Amino acid sequence: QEDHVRSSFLLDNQNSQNTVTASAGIAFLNIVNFKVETDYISQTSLTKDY
Amino acid sequence: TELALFSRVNGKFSTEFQRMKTLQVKDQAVTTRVQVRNRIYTVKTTPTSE
């Protein structure tokens, strides 16, 4: 009896997260007030097997 | 965005955009082969056969 077994596993994974929070707040002497903010969240995952 | 004028006129403007995506692929390929070969007897003719 001859037996051969060959297993091979490959796994790959990659995550990329970006966050950008840009804010601007102007406040005069109780006459003019302007508050702005910008949030940007991005996230990509990728897994690959074999 | 928040804008206040004269400490009496208020304006708020809140926008949001979520965009999610998902891609999955799965492949599979199984191959099997069984070969069997029995050889039990060997039947030959006698040299004195007519």
Image: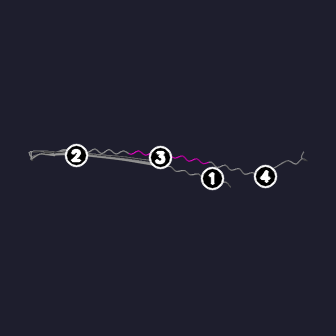
Nearer mark to the viewer, of 1 and 3: 1
Q: Which residue is mark 3?
A: B26
Q: Which residue is mark 2?
A: A23
* Horizontal side of residue B22 vs B14, given as left or right: right
Spatial CA span between label 4 and label 2 = 92 Å
Is the same chain shared between marks 2 and 3?
no
**Residue B29 part of the magenta segment:** yes
Q: Which residues are magenta?
A: B22-32
Spatial CA span between label 1 and label 4 = 31 Å
Residue type, mark 4 in image: Tyr
Look at the magenta stretch and give its main secondary structure: loop
Residue drawn at (64%, 49%) of the image: B34
Residue A4: image tag: 1
In this rendered view, identify the residue nearer to me: A25 or A3: A25
In x, y percent, where is residue A15? 39, 48
Residue type, mark 3 in image: Lys
Residue type, mark 2 in image: Ser
Nearer mark to the viewer, of 4 and 3: 3
Is the same chain shared between marks 1 and 3?
no
**Chain under callout 3:** B
Residue type, mark 1 in image: His
